Length: 166
Length: 93
Ligand SMILES: Nc1nc2c(ncn2[C@@H]2O[C@H](COP(=O)(O)OP(=O)(O)OP(O)(O)=S)[C@@H](O)[C@H]2O)c(=O)[nH]1
Ligand SMILES: [Mg+2]
Image (cartoon, rainbow over all chains, first blue to last red; front, side):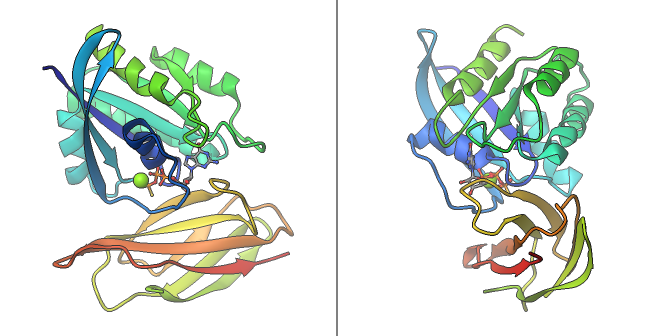
C-alpha cells in the first residue's frame, strides 16, 4: 500500500495543527498549543485508490536549517499554509518555497498554497493576491477553515493528486 | 505560568517592545501572540523568537486599541515535551 509523505509548513499560529487534526481526527482544536513536532499516519481512499498519509505537522517559523532541511528532504508534498488575517504569514510563503526548492534542487515540487481561517470576518490578505501568487508558482490555491472544515479534505487530497501527477 | 513578569517596556502607536523573565530550564523557543482583547478563536497573530531571547517587538498594531499579548514557552526535558502554561497581559485602549 502506497505511502505519501506530506509536510505542512507555514508561520506560527496559522492553523497547520488544526488543519491536520481536522483531517485525521475530524475535530476542531480551539486551544492554541504551539507545536514542536507531530507526526500522523492515516489510511484513506482518494479517488478510489487506497493509500497511507504520513503527515508531518511542523513548527512554524523554524529557526534552525538543520531541522528544516531534514523534513524538506523527505517530504514528497508540501502544504504551504498562511492565515488570511496575517499578512506577514502570506509574505513568508515565498521563503518556505525557496527553502524547499533549495533542498530539493528543483522548481517542480508538489505543493499547494493554503489560505486558512476563511471563517474570519476581518481579513487582511485578499483572495486575488493569493490566487496571483499561486498562479506565478504554478500550483493550486485552496481557501480553508479548520473551524468549519471548508476545504480541508480538498487541500490534502489535492496535494496527493499533485504528487500522483508529477 | 512559566515565563514570568511579562511587561511592556517601550511603546509607539503601532508597536510594542515586551520583556519577560526566562525560567530555570532551557527553552527551545518562545511564541508571542497578540490580538484584540476578547478576540474569538483564531483572531490573533503570532511569531516565534529563540529561547535565548527575553524580549520581542510587535509591529502593525492599530493605534489606541486594547490588545491581549501572550507568551508561550516550549522545549524538551527528560520528562518529555515541556509545555507550560503561557502568561498574558493587556495593553492600550
Ligand atoms: N477561527 C479560526 N481559528 C482557527 C483556524 N485554524 C486554527 N485556528 C486557531 O488558531 C490557533 C492556532 O492554530 P494551530 O493549528 O495550533 O497553529 P499552528 O500553525 O499549528 O501553530 P504552530 O504549531 O506552528 S506555533 C488555535 O487557537 C486554533 O484554534 C481556523 O480556520 N479558524
Ligand atoms: Mg501546530
